[PDB]
Structures are given as C-alpha cells and as structure tokens.
Amino acid sequence: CGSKRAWCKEKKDCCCGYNCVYAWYNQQSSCERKWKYLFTGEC
Image (tube, one colour):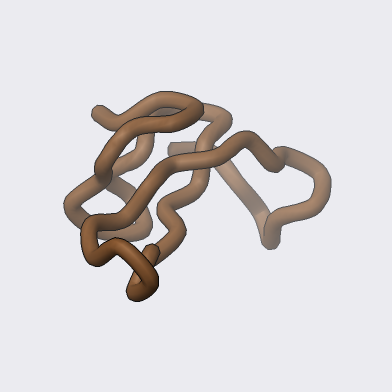
C-alpha cells in the first residue's frame, strides 16, 4: 500500500491512515495522511 508520499492504485490502495491523491501535474497518485479529516476512514 502507498504510505505518506507513495503512489497508490485507488482510494483504498493507500496504507492505513493515508488517502490517495491524484497528481495530474505529475501523473501517478501520492498517498497522504488524514484520519479525522476524512469521511469514516478505516483502510
């Protein structure tokens, strides 16, 4: 799974406690933290 700073496959592909962000500016998606700041959660 992609952890903070790490390519992910989809929204659930980021390591637990990390979300997936699409980086169109550089393609690929980089995972980034966010727990309370995200709906429900649980990866």
